[PDB]
Length: 307
Length: 309
Ligand SMILES: [Cl-]
Ligand SMILES: [Cl-]
Image (cartoon, rainbow over all chains, first blue to last red; front, side, top):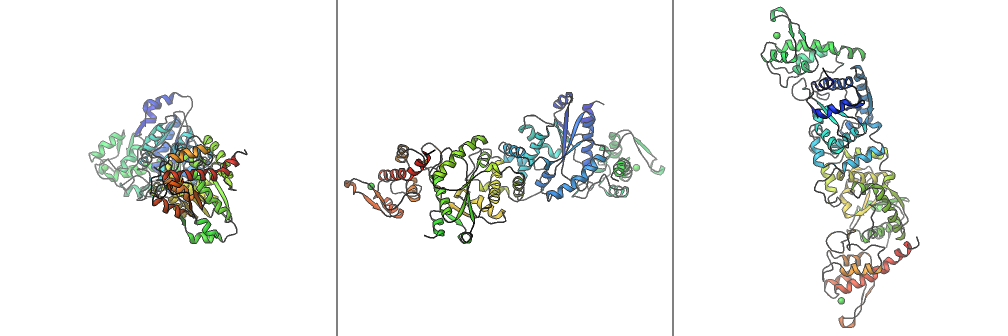
């Protein structure tokens, strides 16, 4: 599979494919993604880190922005407390097999010239565009604060200062990335990953929301949380267990069953798993079992390294 | 008059008088005011500088914030160009008899810890409060920018960093100052000066052609601009010529007339001038003449002191 298609695999969109092809021709190119420090690193994070690894294997230099000041502007508590959580997150990412340069926002987002450019960009960005960009990012507030509208300008400015060719993030980042394309001299190529559904099945996977598989969860917690997960028979849309099968397991896949339920079963693609599950030829509990045991094996090297 | 009443004279309000009395008891206290560098320094500026001089005479150390970065955030062009205009403004203020420390915003408004506090204050200030505070300050924009709401937070943060007891400004600053009182550990006492009407009579005094008297204008420009000014007979409200009489002239005042129109008249207070003008016992042209000649005399010491350099 070529570089382009490796990068495209399991993304929701690329802005634009044509521009990505131009970036691939360069001898040196770079990609970044930002993570607000999180107490738990979960499959949400891991999906995006896998995408960064795809880019790394395609010749990109990778920058992970440990986005302490962004999270501070997004109301995540005190800044020194936001910094302690990021130190752990770094170790987890290294344990996932990513080799990258790690930058804390605070190392450069308070420098004189960075700040002056925030204000320069603030003169060019409408309140309406700033607020629009934060709808899927800002926490649900009845009295929105000025911090909401500084945040997107700071993300845009960070992309400018990083000098990257590609910016990666979730689909929730879409409008901030579009602003960056309008506001900056160099149009950044944007790769968006899908939003993983949480295990409760009623929103995104989140650390604050308690509906996550952490990459360092122990095997019994992986089993318990998968067993309890939303997984309606025949239904693929909004089904977090099928999403995990899609984005994390490897095919062909051997799903172990007792012989009384049909015996062990081989599935050559996600699309085939989808077909079996839609037709109720595979029951929730048995998908869950397979997904739990596979995820335990996939996450083992990460648990081992973290120690 | 005592210190309190000298300070109060010709102010629109004091937030609060009770707190100002407490500040007056301190051995050391300080006041600031911010000016976006302006190519013309006019009676608008001079009214406020006179107020800073009142505070200086009452024992306050004075800080004039030459607000280059505020003006930059308020769309006044390039920053180095905004800085050149401020250097001239400094000389004018010294020539008005003010002895004060002059601070450029850019010397401290980009420091790491200042900036961090802007963001800290941004987490506490509602968009609605920020926009409300800028209605009478922000330039006329069909697509209002994010800079509009950072600006008041930066003014608040400047007041915090200056460490001042009193913040002075026009009534247009009112809501930013109220935000400062809510946002900061130390409640700053706010003294607001009235907004001078422009000579056209259709907004505030600003560097619109023939809408200002500059403190360094030559005598013929002072006469021409006063002669042309909005000054409707009998009407004091919104009348820039009566405002100038109020806030700048000395009483008793001798207004010259020919004997056929009632002869020369002596006016011992502004209130007396007001009475005469409301009752049409003094005609616009004659008020104008007196106001022009008085202003030439009042501004003479400023012209003189600027002609040393
Ligand atoms: Cl089954
Ligand atoms: Cl008369």
